[PDB]
Image (cartoon, coloured by chain):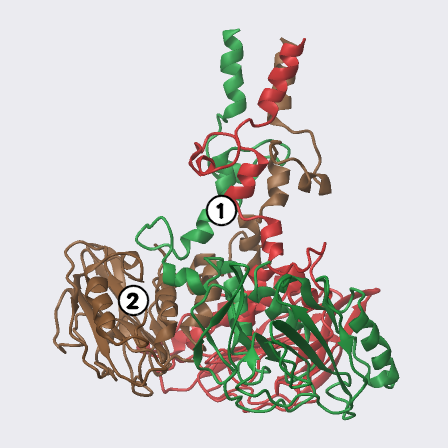
Chain colours: A green, B red, C brown
Amino acid sequence: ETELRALKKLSTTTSRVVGDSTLALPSNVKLSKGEVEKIAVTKKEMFDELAQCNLPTIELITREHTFNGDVIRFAAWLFLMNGQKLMIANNVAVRMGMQYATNLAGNNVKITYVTSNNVVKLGHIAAGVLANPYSNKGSGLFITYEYNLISNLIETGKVCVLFITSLSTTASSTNSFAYSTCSVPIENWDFNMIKLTAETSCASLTAMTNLVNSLVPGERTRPVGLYVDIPGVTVTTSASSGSLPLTTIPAVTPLIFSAYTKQVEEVGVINTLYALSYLP
Amino acid sequence: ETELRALKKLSTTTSRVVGDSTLALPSNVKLSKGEVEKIAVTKKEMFDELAQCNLPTIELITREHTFNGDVIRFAAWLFLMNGQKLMIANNVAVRMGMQYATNLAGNNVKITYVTSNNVVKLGHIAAGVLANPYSNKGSGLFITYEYNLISNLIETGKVCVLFITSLSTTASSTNSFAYSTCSVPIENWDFNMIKLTAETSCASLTAMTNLVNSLVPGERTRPVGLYVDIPGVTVTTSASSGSLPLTTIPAVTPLIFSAYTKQVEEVGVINTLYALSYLP
Amino acid sequence: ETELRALKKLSTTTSRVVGDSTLALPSNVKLSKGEVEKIAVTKKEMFDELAQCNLPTIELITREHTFNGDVIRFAAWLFLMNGQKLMIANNVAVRMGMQYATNLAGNNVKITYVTSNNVVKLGHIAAGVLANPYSNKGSGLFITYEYNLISNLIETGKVCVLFITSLSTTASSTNSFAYSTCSVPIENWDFNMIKLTAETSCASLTAMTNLVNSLVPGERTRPVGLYVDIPGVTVTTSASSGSLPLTTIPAVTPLIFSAYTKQVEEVGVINTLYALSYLP
């Protein structure tokens, strides 16, 4: 029975040591920790990027604006946040767990964190003075607090999100524009549930499908529709206006998320920025 | 009877649960899935960045231009594509699987996806009007369809790869430049094979190495040579020019890949952008 | 006897083919290489980003300025290094194992690699002509070789690190500015040790926290203090000057690391850039 004791240890560990052979080990065989350290990218290694002074944790001031050290999302989110050629002025994204966030003009603003049932839900900042109005035919996503941009009316305790778009192709000189809007209660608010989709079926997407079909086949562009998964929200579109719905946003108006692309073809870039901005 | 049964499962799975000690387990020890789910960053976690509404897959429109979710790749490729300080005008990279791609001027246009044997291989777009001609001691890589920038002669069923370079350093006011053009058939085309190398031996590097020797000893620069692994390729490197072989690209000229840097000293980033752009 | 050899294989090999089932296998269940090949993003895949022509290793020139393939390290570091707004002129960071590095004006220059006891400790370059004076009410980190920026005196065989800051908030019109300085020998030099912290206790932080506390309510800002882990280090923090200590630096003055943000609120990006720039 003592043979069982020794032969049992063969299960616990491997006689093999780490090395180049670990790369060439056949796929069917099992692995030890040392080899798995080599083969797969370790969570330590990503944590090792910002590690200084061999501290147990990375610097607090760094963890604030790096999504608590999630470097992978931080890199891609950073460029789309600002520096894109086609984005007008500076896209405004209020990331959670932050002291300051830039506004449309570019001044960093102390963020008013809204607390829901003793839990911080989201924060907003003053819009500031927009550099320029949104000129060309492009799409954009807008999220504001206690305000409706189309109606210019304030609803206390309610968050309204607007999506604007240009149906016509940028090359096509014909001008057709529409938008989708909805108001969400403060309580059941989750950034994850909202997205811009071209495949998932929703009421906004249905409107865009036939609305583009209204235009000539040469100038058609694939529909991009607002989708909201949260209970208690109704998405309302608009008829084909043919003129841009929103040109500028007042500074006094509270702001949560706002991003517009000069051309419509890079509409999906907006959704990517929204996806990266808030962790689910 | 049951002693074999239990002892097999005893070895087969792990009794230990995940925790802090999971990090401190011996390297030679073997591990469970929950342990590996902690130690290494997962496919899901990388996939989790773009996940919305807990959907099985990422959004289609985001899936198109993010290399089908290669967020690790997408971030680095993005800045080199747009916003490089030394890059002139807008370098053009045509990403596969996408409807639109920006041209030199910055106006995004529809892509003509070439299909070979009922299988797509590459896409090209109109060059557009260049913002400014390339005027400095710099190097660039150029890929065009059905055309030869050296001879300005149209091709049929042929894709020509051109690589200009700056023999002198930035400080060396002495002016001398060379190039290495190649033409490849569509049938044998494969992006991954071609690269810019300073160590791998090739015909272009063979000439390029001696060319800097013609320079004064103080003026030497590290050779950078075009290398093509595609069988049936012809590589030609002309003598020193003393002037820029190419100044501007005609708008009607078809384009696939084009990028140039004012300073030759950053020629390496050109290869990186080409490496990032196309998945092997 | 045969059972022992037979049952050993059951230990070493899972005998289960990879698939979606492997994705859904229980966490307690042990797994083979094929699962870890799937479950975790491999070191191979990160190598695959720059992989080309199926070469056993990545290109030399590409690996030189990409931290030898640390793509994610290269990604986030790239945008912060240059191209971001709220950065005066160009941030200058000299990466190790490099031929050229950009100056303040943006022209890349040869790097004098300082080798100590037959080990290359660091490298420095000529500062070049600064584009503009260092704006207003911002913070920055400065590292110079054989020099003292505040004292403008040469110290052979000693490297000095300087930190500047603005106590007052950008919104507050009141003006209060302080700084921290240290002189480090080259022999004990190690990049990873030094950092900007808001939680770790250090002499520089202790001097600064009461200083901003001396400011009236509503004007106080989170203290960010120099912390140096290298033994034999002195840190000095003067009284609140009320005016910017430094505006421009001479071109002839050697420069190791230099970064400055127009707004103080983005102090973290300064530490973030330093953390990314040099591997531990």
Left or right, C152 with respect to A17, comes to: left
Task: Tell me if residue B57 can be seen.
Answer: yes
Residue B164, given in percent of the width and then of the height, sits at 53, 79
Which quadrant holds residue A148?
Answer: bottom right
Query: Which of the two residues, C145 or B192, is positioned nearer the viewer here?
Result: C145
Left or right, B98 with respect to C246, comes to: right
Q: How many residues crowd around disc 1 within 10 Å: few (fewer than 14), some, or many (20 or more)? A: many
Question: The numbered mark 2 sits on a residue in which chain?
Answer: C
> What is the C-alpha distance between the residues marked 1 and 2?
31 Å
Judging by the rendered image, the residue that carries numbered circle 2 is C224
Name the mark on residue A42: 1
| Circles 1 and 2: CB atoms closer than 8 Å | no
Residue C34, given in percent of the width and then of the height, sits at 64, 39
Residue C71, given in percent of the width and then of the height, sits at 49, 60
Compared with A68, A138 (above or below) is below
- Amino acid type, mark 2: Val
Which quadrant holds residue A261?
Answer: bottom right
Name the mark on residue C211: none
